Length: 288
Length: 290
Ligand SMILES: C=C(C)CCOP(=O)(O)OP(=O)(O)O
Ligand SMILES: C=C(C)CCOP(=O)(O)OP(=O)(O)O
Ligand SMILES: C=C(C)CCOP(=O)(O)OP(=O)(O)O
Ligand SMILES: C=C(C)CCOP(=O)(O)OP(=O)(O)O
Ligand SMILES: [Mg+2]
Ligand SMILES: [Mg+2]
Ligand SMILES: [Mg+2]
Ligand SMILES: [Mg+2]
Ligand SMILES: [Mg+2]
Ligand SMILES: [Mg+2]
Image 1 (cartoon, rainbow over the protein chains, first blue to last red):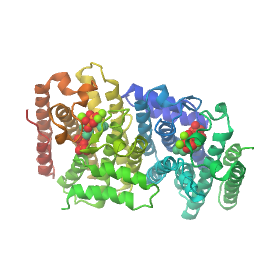
Image 2 (cartoon, chains in turn red, orange):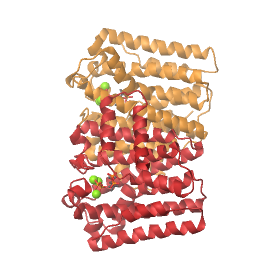
Image 3 (cartoon, rainbow over the protein chains, first blue to last red):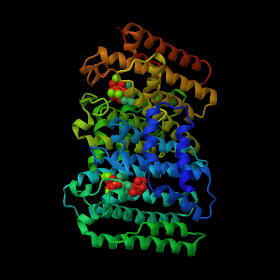
Image 4 (cartoon, protein in one colour):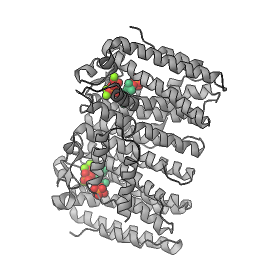
């Protein structure tokens, strides 16, 4: 239902204006339709719902904007000059399906279009401006793209945990923290609560990358939908490479536990029903 | 008042230096392309329209101008890439990917796109104004604007198409981000719908004209003049104005387009509190002779 509606919202954005380049629209939609867990938009919508706010088309637009930036980031991450994968979401990567130019531009479209999507909501305009500012912050030079540069620069280097945390909190952490913070902001919560939601999001965001690192070296192709073990060949700074699998599994499980405990704590202090968020977090757990 | 070019660049610099650095290499790559050069026509036109409308310039106007220049800059970085136009030179210097590497250039362009909206949301404009500016800048830049035009441009390589299809490419890849500063300044000025449409119209005329001009320069001017490799359009079999219509008719179209834009601007000056002399002088600097 949420899943279906998120994809409807994205399809609507691309199919309700007069088309300029049919090939561009097709390339953008290819990557969207290839698959994806939709964790980021789902979390935004679940927090709104948990905070007792009926979901509207505007919430789905805000959620879609977040997913659009996430999708653009994947398309560029996969490119030959970056991680160079032939597969994403169980299908050919955008650049192998089409060509590199098309993939570069499809990613660019998603980044630029995302802010138009976000600006189409019926939220109060002060809310919208804050969401735009924060989404830029999470995504750009001081967020995801900054993290991506650090990830590429760390290849083959012996970095420490602080530096590994810096990569992971930025390349992945920021865009998983944003949906928690953004939902709280739309709910117009006070500063203390906005900080607690950002904290939960930052814990989930770092844990998600620890999880992604573990899966890179433990899972098969069918399970992850991308070529396994690229992190090893590329000499990426990762949790397993720095700390080992045993510690990485412990950190993932502890982090997920902590996020859940903070969520349950909130429900003692405000009108907040986190059961769906808790269910989603449970589905992220791994077994060695 | 202040030199606009220097203030625009200082505004962009401050955006990158006012927050704790995450990747120094990224900041360096972004600023390299900004600092390489550029006429800054897009942000200058926005600022000139604000001033022509008798509005004193503020930090916020420079931020909005800077955001536009950031998107424009990101578009050049990606346009130069090996998978796209494959130029080794831009703004008289090595292109971003030849100075650094392909990955760096991809990410530098991505940064500029994503950062631009953060820049725009830093203004002190009324929030309803900012939301409209964000929506419109996305429209001008994305799948229905610049990027859409970029895809059409690559798809038309080696293809014979008509004027209609050539205009579709040009209006979207270049027209929209030259139309935006006119529309956006009128929007910040809070002009009525009719005036917003008139300013957009002026900008679309100037925007289409600027690409005709660019097409003409790519085949008539040398490397020293344009700061990029001449004649790339020819070798890659791009659809251009001189190819579709000949050089003579292309010069004629440029001149008459710039005439048309100037006429609308003069008419507005006879109707509202608007003083476009500096805009008109900028437009005159865009003229070419055979
Ligand atoms: C680890 C990161 C940040 C990239 C993959 O994210 P996901 O694992 O959420 O990818 P999809 O489900 O969207 O394919
Ligand atoms: C912005 C991104 C893609 C962060 C996750 O990095 P990875 O390169 O490990 O993600 P996957 O390709 O493994 O999904
Ligand atoms: C839209 C086009 C023709 C790309 C180059 O734009 P400019 O000719 O304005 O480039 P800079 O001055 O910014 O270098
Ligand atoms: C979005 C852009 C960059 C439009 C100009 O494309 P061109 O490829 O014609 O411009 P130059 O490289 O000649 O500046
Ligand atoms: Mg990567
Ligand atoms: Mg990757
Ligand atoms: Mg990975
Ligand atoms: Mg080009
Ligand atoms: Mg080019
Ligand atoms: Mg050109």
